[PDB]
Image: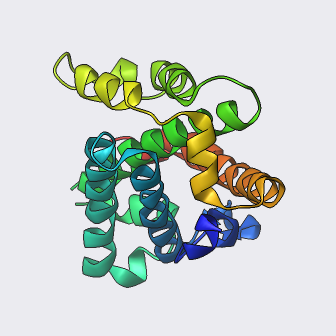
Amino acid sequence: TFLETFKKSFVDVPIDAEKGNAISTAEFLEAAESLTTMFDVLGSIAFSPVKTDMLGNVEKIRKRMLAAPLESQNIQDLVRNELKTSHTATEGLLWLVRGLEFTCIALSKNIGSTEELADSFRGSYRVTLKPHHSFLVKPIFSAAMSACPYRKDFYAKLGDDEQKVQEELREYLVALDKIVNILKRFLESKEAKW
């Protein structure tokens, strides 16, 4: 299946429940980068702005990790220790998590309904990224989502066995949603404000 091509799944990103659901930085960034390959499946050209945006935010985080590695081993510590300085990686995390949630809601909505892909994406956009985007960025996202493939064509690209693709994508989305929820709670805390 397409999902088995992933360098890193969100299923395999470590979470340290004893240290406040510490999300391991390296595996998380690799998982975010793998998820961007799904934009190519959906519409290489159409979703290139979303991929580019997401990859830029990943890179902001990676830059900081590399510059301060012992202080940046999990996402929460990475943020705590940058916020004595620069908020570049922290701000990158904010926007990455919004992009991950946009993708997560859209796909979860679509697989749990018969809606067309374009509408699952539109409804997700409304509740994730749209309120934070400028008047010039909204039309970029709107044009991209209108160019979604027909849902049948999308899932066929994910593998030949409809049942296996669905079970595996659900497991993936559940794991992503868990990580999104943890990081959103972290980001809304005073700990993460600059």
Query: In percent of the image, x 45 and y 46: which residue is there?
Result: 42
Viewer-proximal residue among 78 and 94: 94
Quadrant housing the C terminus: top left
Q: How is the image coloured?
A: rainbow
Q: Tell me which corner region of the image, top left, top right, bottom left or bottom right, holds residue 94.
A: top left
Q: Which quadrant is home to the N terminus? A: bottom right
Of residues 136 and 88, the one nearer the viewer is 136
Taking the view exactly as shown, the residue that stands out farthest to the bottom is 70
In-image side of 85 versus 12 (left or right): left
Q: Is residue 95 visible?
A: yes
Camera-nearest residue between 85 and 130: 130
**x then y, percent, for residue 138:** 27, 21
- As drawn, 41 above or below 103: below
Q: Is residue 15 left or right of residue 161?
A: left
Residue 84 is situated, as x and y percent measured from the top left of the image, at: 29, 60
Residue 93, image x, y percentages = 39, 51
Q: Residue at x 30, y 39 (%)?
A: 46
In this view, the residue in front, 154 or 87, is 154
Q: Is residue 138 above or below residue 88?
A: above
Give x and y (percent) for residue 44: 33, 50
| Residue 189 in view | no
Please state the total of marks drawn on the protein image.
0
**Which quarter of the picture shows residue 146?**
top left
On the picture, is 92 further left or further right than 170? left
